[PDB]
Image (cartoon, rainbow over all chains, first blue to last red):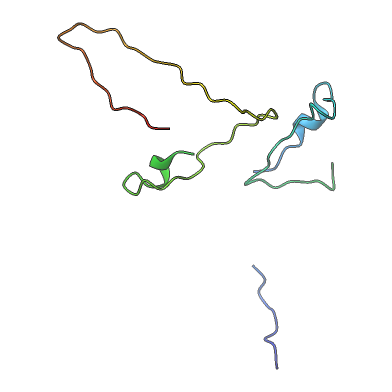
Length: 44
Length: 50
């Protein structure tokens, strides 16, 4: 089958807690949720 | 989760806010709340069901 050619292809998550404050122990590990924001894991 | 924000009339529930707690809570305890008033102005309130 033929396939149509693709054309016309169509805030800020903050990893601040990880770099701020004393790091927690593995049992007391700090967990955070990111939603509706643009993360930059590669930069981190 | 607050039902009123997504639809006051519907009664459907949506997650209004998120609070981050690492600890997992196993027990639920209800704190009784009482408002002092004069006998003439005494107020009766609907019970909440868990």
